[PDB]
Amino acid sequence: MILIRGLTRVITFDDQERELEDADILIDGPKIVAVGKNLSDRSVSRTIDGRGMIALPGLINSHQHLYEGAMRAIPQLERVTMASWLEGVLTRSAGWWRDGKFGPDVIREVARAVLLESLLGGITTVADQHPFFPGATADSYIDATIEAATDLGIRFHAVRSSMTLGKSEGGFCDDLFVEPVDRVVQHCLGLIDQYHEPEPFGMVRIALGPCGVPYDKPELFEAFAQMAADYDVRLHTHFYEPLDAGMSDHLYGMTPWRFLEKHGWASDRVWLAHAVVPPREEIPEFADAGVAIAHLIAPDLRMGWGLAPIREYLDAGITVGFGTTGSASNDGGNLLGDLRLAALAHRPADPNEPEKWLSARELLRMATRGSAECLGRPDLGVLEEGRAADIACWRLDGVDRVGVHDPAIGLIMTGLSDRASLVVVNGQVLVENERPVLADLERIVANTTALIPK
Amino acid sequence: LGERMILIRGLTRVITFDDQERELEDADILIDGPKIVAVGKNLSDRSVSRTIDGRGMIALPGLINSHQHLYEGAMRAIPQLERVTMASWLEGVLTRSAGWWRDGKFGPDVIREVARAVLLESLLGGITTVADQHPFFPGATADSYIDATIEAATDLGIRFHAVRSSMTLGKSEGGFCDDLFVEPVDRVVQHCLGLIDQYHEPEPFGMVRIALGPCGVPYDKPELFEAFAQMAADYDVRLHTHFYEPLDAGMSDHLYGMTPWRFLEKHGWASDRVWLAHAVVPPREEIPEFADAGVAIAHLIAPDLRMGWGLAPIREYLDAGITVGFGTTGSASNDGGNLLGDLRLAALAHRPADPNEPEKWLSARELLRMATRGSAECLGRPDLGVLEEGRAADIACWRLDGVDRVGVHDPAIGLIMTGLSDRASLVVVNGQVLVENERPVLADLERIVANTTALIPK
C-alpha cells in the first residue's frame, strides 16, 4: 500500500465536509483504505511526505474537447460571438480532416498533451466530447482519445457526440456536417460494447452526447434515452445557451427543457452543460427531475454569454459540477485556474448581497464531488475509505502563498501557478514534484507539436 | 560601448510595444549596463560578456504593477473577508492593520519581510516595477513603512515606486479616517519632502521614486490635494488617488456639492502629472474631460470584481485616447500579486457587457500593453515599458514550449489565454538578471519564505 503522511490540510468533501490537519491518506491498489491522523505504515510499500501540502479529491473536468488543443490562441477566433466561433472551429476541423492533417495519429497525440496538462493541473478524471469535429467518427477519434488516456493512466469518460440536424431542416449545424441518426446510434452501441467499464473504479466509460436541441434530431434524443436505460450509461447535452430558447420555440414550439422532458431526458441519468439562461420557473423542475449541471465559466465569459444562475441551482439542491470546455474556447485545460474566474466574476451580479456569491469551498466541491455526480461516479470526488484513490495535492509553502490564512481559499485566490505537486489516479502516482513520473514530458511536447496542423 | 554587455539570443517572439507596435521573430536583445542597446535579428556579440539562449521564449517589456499594498501580503485568504462589500472589507483591513500595529506585531522588521516576499513573487511573475501604496494601514508613517519596503525592494533589485498615502479628513468632518488616526496636512507634507530628499532618483533609469497619494476625495482634505499639486510641480513627482469607486459621487456631493472630478479639477489635480485608481463609475460626459486633462487611469480588474463593483469602461477610455495601465492592488483584495494572471480575468470578464459587439472587447495585445507601456505612462516613466534602444533593460520572458501551451498559434494571445502557470522564465531589471529558469538568481527563496512566514501576525 501507499501512505501519504503529514498532509498539512486534507479536504474530504465527505458528507460532514470534514477537513483534517497534519493527517494521512492510506492507499491500497485502486482504493483509499483510510483518512486520518497517524495512520499505520505496517503494510506500506512506500510513504510519501505530505508535509506542506493541501490534499483534495482529484479534480474532475466534466467537459473537454481534446481535439481543440490544436486550436489555441488563433487570432481570428480571439473576440467572436458564438456563431462566428462555431463556424471558424467547424471549418478548421473539417478542412484539416479533409486535407489529411487531422488523422487518428494526430488526435491521439493532441489528446495525450492535453490530458497530460490535465494531470499536471491536478485533474484525475476527464470527460471528453467532440461536438465541433464533424469527421470525428470517420476519424476513429474516440479510439484514439481512449488510447492516449489509457497510456497516461488518467481516468476517462468518452462522450460520443454528434450534430444530426442539418441546416436544411433548421439546424445551426449545416448539412455538410451531419450523420444519419442510425449511424450515430449503431456506432454508440459498438463503443459501449468495446470500451465501457461499468464496475466501481472503472477507468474508461462511454456516455451519449447530442450537441443540443438546436443541433440534433428529436429521434436521436429518444434513441439515446432508450440506450442509456438498456446499457446503464449517462446522457449529456448542452443546455440553455443564449440562442437556444428561440431556436427551440421556432423548430418545436417549446422550451429546451420541455423538449428534453418530451424526449426522455428529464431524468437522473443526465448532466447538462452551461445552463446559462433558463427561465427561473423551470429551475425547481430541474431539481425534481434529478438532472445535473456543469458550470463552464470560462467559455460563458469568452463568448459574451454571462453568468449562469449557480446560486439558484445550489439553493434548489441541483448537482453542480465544473468544466473547462475545449481549448478553442478557454483556451487552456486549467480547471483550478478557471475556479478563480467564477469566484470573482459572479460577484458584480449581486453587489450588495455577498452571501449569494460562490465561495472557494463551494467551487472546489463543484470541481470534485459535483463533477463526480455529473458523471455518475459515486466512487469518485471524495477522500474517504472505500472511494477511488484519485488524489490531487498542491504545495502551500511557496513564496507566492506566504500570508495565506485559509489554504482552501488560498488555492483559488492566490498563486503564480496552479501546477499540482502530487497526483494519484487509481492508486498510481502519476505526478510528483510537479512532474510526470511515468510520462516523458519533453518527448510528448516535441511529438505533439510536430503534428499540430500548419 | 562596454565589454560587459549581455545578449539574449534567438527569442522566438519579441513584443516591443514601440510606437510602431513592432514584433520580431527569432530575434535578439542587447544590453549594456542599465539600458537596452539594440533590438533585432543577428545582433553582434563582439562587446558581449554573456549570451543567453532565448530560444522557445516570448519576450516582453517587464510588467509594471501600478498598484500594490505590500502590507496586505499578511492578510491573504482570511475567511471573514472572503465575501464582503467594500464597507465590511475596509473595516476588516483597517481593524487588522491598526490592531496588529498597536499590538506590536507589525513593526518595520515584519513589514520588510512581508514586502520582500511579495516583491519576490512579483519578480517571479515577470513584474519588474512595482508602485506600492498604504491607504489602509493608518500607522504606516509612524511605523517607518516606506523605509522598510524600500529596503526590501533595493535588496531584491526590483524597480520601485513608493506612494506616500494618507487619510487626512477625520471622522469628525465626515471621513472614514478616524480622529485617532488623522495626520495634520503639514506633517504629511513634511514627511513627503523628507522621503523625496532621502530616496527619490529622478534621473533616467532611477530605481526608487516617490509619489504622492491621498486615498481619495471622500478621505482627504482639499488642502492636501493643493499642497501635493504644488509639490508635484516643485519636484516633478507623480500624483495618485483613487477615482470613481462606487459611492464616491454621493460622498463628494454631500461634502462639496460637486463631482469627484470637479473637485479634482478645482484643486489642481486635472493634469498630466496624475494617475487614478479603478475609475469604475464616472459620469460618461466627464470622460472627454479626463482625456483633455491628460490624466492616466489604472485598471484594477481583480478588486473591482472581488468587491462586486463591476467593469470600468476601459474601452471608452482607450477610445478617448486616455492612458490605461494595470495593477493588482493589495493581497487582501486579490488575493495574489499575479498581474499576468489578472489580465486573463479582464480579457474574459468585460465580454458579457457587450455580448454582440466583440470589437469592443479588450484584446490580449491591448491588455499586455496596459501591463507594460500603459503602467509605465501611469508612473511617469518614459524610460520603461518598451523594448527599444535607449530604454531601460527591464525585460520579462516566458517559455512557450510547455505541454500546456502546445497548439498555441499566437504567443501573445497564448500568454493570456493558456497555461497552468504564469511563472516567468527570465527576468531582467536595470540590466541585472534576477530570475532565470524560473528561479531567483540572487534571492534565497527558501530562507525568505521561512523568515516571512515566522513573522506574519498570529
Image (cartoon, coloured by chain):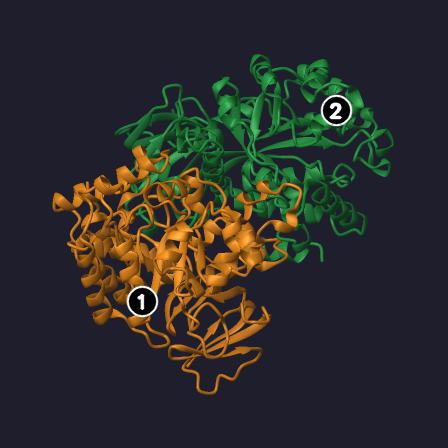
Chain colours: A orange, B green
Q: Is residue B40 toward the left or the right of residue A276 in the image?
A: left
Q: Examine the rendered structure and indicate whether residue B417 appears above or below residue A370.
A: above
Answer left or right for A165 relative to A244: left
Amino acid type indicated by mark 2: Ser
In the picture, the disc for residue A228 is 1
Residue B106's x, y, as percent? 74, 48
Label 2: which residue? B252
Q: Quadrant of residue A375?
A: bottom left
Image coordinates for residue B45, horizontal then vertical, percent = 29, 31
Q: Is residue B360 visible?
A: yes
Three-letter amino acid code of the residue under disc 1: Ala
Quarter-wise, where is residue A210 in the image? bottom left
* Residue located at (32% from left, 69% from top): A229
Which quadrant, please, contains the C terminus of chain A? top left
Image mark 1: chain: A
Image coordinates of residue A228 in percent, x first then y, are 31, 67
Q: Residue A334, image x and y in percent?
A: 41, 52
Query: In the figure, residue B361 lies in which quadrant?
Result: top left
In the foreground, A153 or A430: A153
Foreground residue, B159 or B287? B287
Q: Residue at x 63, y 42 (%)?
A: B70
Q: Is residue B447 visible?
A: no
User: In terms of secondary structure, where does tag 1 sit?
Assistant: helix
The quarter of the rendered structure image containing the N terminus of chain A is bottom left
Question: From what the image shows, is residue A401 above or below residue A46?
Answer: above
Outermost residue on the top side: it is B292
- Give me the C-alpha separation between circle 2 and circle 1: 63 Å
